[PDB]
Image (cartoon, rainbow over all chains, first blue to last red; front, side, top):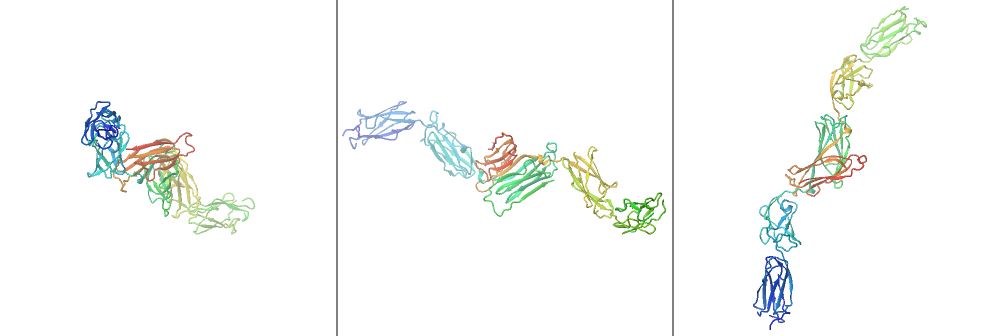
Length: 308
Length: 306
């Protein structure tokens, strides 16, 4: 029970793709039709954008272990013959891919710059190959360890963007320092690791208008800006206000100022007089909050302040 | 002469004052004539006793004076040989005499005046007894001098109650000597120096700048105590001129200071990290939309902090 060319396959990781300095293994399974223990007709040759002498470490039972490691290139032909016959696998062609580079690959994003404690930090890893070019696709094993305040671990989420890019996300609940180490093949890649600062983070949507100020520039009978004060200055705000505080100030230099902290739900109208006459565009209307969720047991009063 | 056809006339037999001379003249007729005889007699009955001085005449006229000393109502008899003359007895009301040491003036036009508005005060006539005059017909006068020895005419009105309203124009800044008089004597606290100042013209004035300041809060519901946050300010509208500024007061407060000149309706977006605040946007209205430039197409002015 000498061999069969045909009913005897071959299989393995490495007759399916490749990588620049990584070993490419596969296994021959000799059959007659069925079964097997160490006859020796098989022979492998590999031509491609290099030379490649492949080892056929061979036999025991009717199996054979072949390995070759491509030295950086794309497509390789593999011919598997049995006593000068084509095994029921071949000829067959694999495509070897370049190899990513530990310090030819970097990361950018606001995630390695400056992080708030109430919004997710982002950034991208950039995959370069051995030579210099940038990786087309993915399947490269990059890793991301995050160690923040109080040493504690932070679980980053790496997303294979199928190009030679991977997206990174993480949450930094506490203000503190965060060490972000991004290794390739367990080797800290471009300028990795690196500290990152996270600070307390304003929360827009729940954030409040405090105070307001508007200034008038008093005009005299000539049509020029006055240069001292002295005029009667009255500011009237009218609306619904769980709270108010208003100010009518004579900045004693030609101008008058109103300073007020107003809070409520609705639309508002402020009357402004200089010597008992409205200024150009008084009153003026505006709106803060929402006239809905607004209280019922609210009046709509009129606050007044006057200056000497 | 005869009682019926001869008649008296004059000021003082028509009304009176206190410490003013009441004067009237008698015309003896026969019918139609007169030269002296005598026959005429006068006595005043009143709240106080009075002695009329009658100056008998050249031609058939008489001159009688009698000034009323205390005041109200006085009766004037006029017999001729014991025979009421054809208008008698008569009734005259002496009113109290205004005093220049007890009448006084008040109004903001004695305090502080603007060069762009009429100044006003009131006179309060007080009588010689220190009782507020009741009614008018008092000859109070007003002399105002302005700053280059200019002359301001004041317009005095007679409130028909013992007071008199006054208005004047102090058209230039400087000082204004206000002097109110009564038959030549300055009333109490006169004259007075009044400072007039340059007046603001409200209807022609407007807004220069604007500011508002948000208290940033974190997630734990508290207020922050420093900055760091991206704070963005955006103004949309028909802006004819504008300047904006987003400021981190680096204490967890942010400020927007802007100067807007425009003719329409405006809204303003305020983002504490790419997320509108508890009112953003707030809409204000400025300048009449109908008068603006026929082409000012509203746009967006944006300014960012961090």
